[PDB]
Image (tube, rainbow, N blue to C red):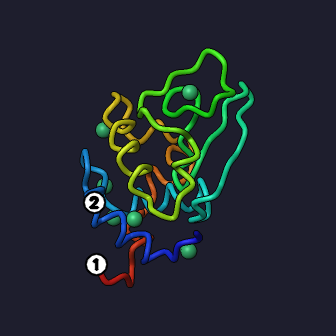
Amino acid sequence: KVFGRCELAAAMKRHGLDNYRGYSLGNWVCAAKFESNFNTQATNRNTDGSTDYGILQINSRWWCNDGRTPGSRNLCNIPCSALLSSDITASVNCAKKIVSDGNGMNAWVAWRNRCKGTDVQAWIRGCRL
Ligand SMILES: [Cl-]
Ligand SMILES: [Cl-]
Ligand SMILES: [Cl-]
Ligand SMILES: [Cl-]
Ligand code: NA
Ligand code: NA
């Protein structure tokens, strides 16, 4: 599923991401834009052999099981393929664990490099929330 900008913002708010650990909703929408272009099916390989899955590009090194990332963990206790569903619940719930892991949203390098220090509220401008 490819979400609209405001459709995704609404779904993330409904799931409690708006100011979760102090990150306003625009941070999450900005991260999703640059991680997946709002596409739940997005997958991308990392140099170490792990893979990133779904709308927030959650990686198989630490957070999910894809059966092909040797030496990895599965801290969200989910198959990585569940993160490609049109229902973003698993991605949001896993994201809540990630962002609570010490480094905040710096865990998403695209957030650090493209969203941090910018006017992230722009990403929800015009949206009925
Ligand atoms: Cl957009
Ligand atoms: Cl914020
Ligand atoms: Cl959903
Ligand atoms: Cl933080
Ligand atoms: Na915001
Ligand atoms: Na894994």
Q: Are the residues flagged by discs 1 and 2 in contact, CB closer than 8 Å? A: yes
Residue situated furthest top in the rendering: 71
Where is residue 57 shown, x and y percent of the image?
57, 47
Residue, x 58% and y 69% (percent of image)? 1
Tell me the quadrant of the picture where the C terminus can be found.
bottom left
Density class for disc 1 (Cα within 10 Å; few <14, some 14-19, many ≥20) is few
Q: Quadrant of residue 98?
A: top left
Residue beneath label 2, please?
A: 18
Residue 123 placed where, x, y %?
44, 70
Instruction: Name the kind of residue labelled 2 in the image.
Output: Asp
- Foreground residue, 124 or 82? 82
Name the secondary structure under disc 1: loop
Tag shown at residue 129: 1
Q: Position of residue 27 (x, y in %)?
A: 40, 57
Mark 2 C-beta closer than 8 Å to ligand 5: yes
The crowding category of the residue bearing disc 2, from other C-alpha atoms within 10 Å (few below 14, some 14 to 19, many at least 20), is: some
- Residue 26 picture quarter: bottom left
Is the residue at mark 1 in contact range of ligand 5, meaning its CB lies under 8 Å from it?
no
Q: Residue at 57%, 20% (x, y): give it.
A: 72
Cα–Cα span, label 1 and label 2: 10 Å
The amino acid type, in three-letter code, at marker 1 is Leu
Q: Which mark is residue 48?
A: none
